[PDB]
Length: 91
DNA sequence: TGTATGTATGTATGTATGCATACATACATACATACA
Image 1 (cartoon, rainbow, N blue to C red):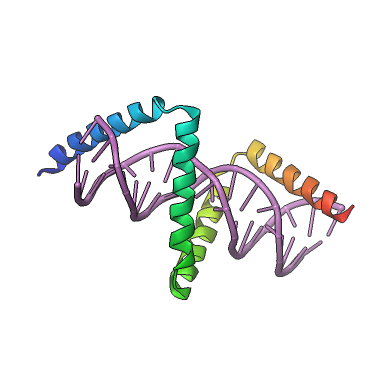
Image 2 (spheres, chains in turn orange, yellow):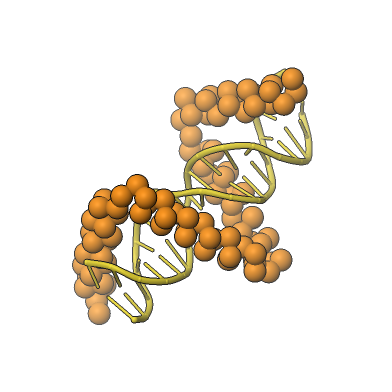
């Protein structure tokens, strides 16, 4: 299959997925997300030490970039949230 | 006290395999811990 053919098959696949999600009830949505959670729990509890260390390292790097791309309003709101949460814990 | 840094949990998105099923990835949300 060519690079072009693959892209057209996958565009269609993505469109059917989009339709199916847009047709879900809120109950179907929440059942889907519960299964996603379980699948992820199950992957994590059998993770090796090394796989864990790689996952955290990537997570700490996704976080760095995300922070670095934040607008000034987003930064500011993030600091407010942390500052209010710290204040609550102190008091 | 407040912000930088780390991570437990959750999910939007894409797709390999049998349009739906059933994962799998990338990345966010939300708090927690380290540190100035």
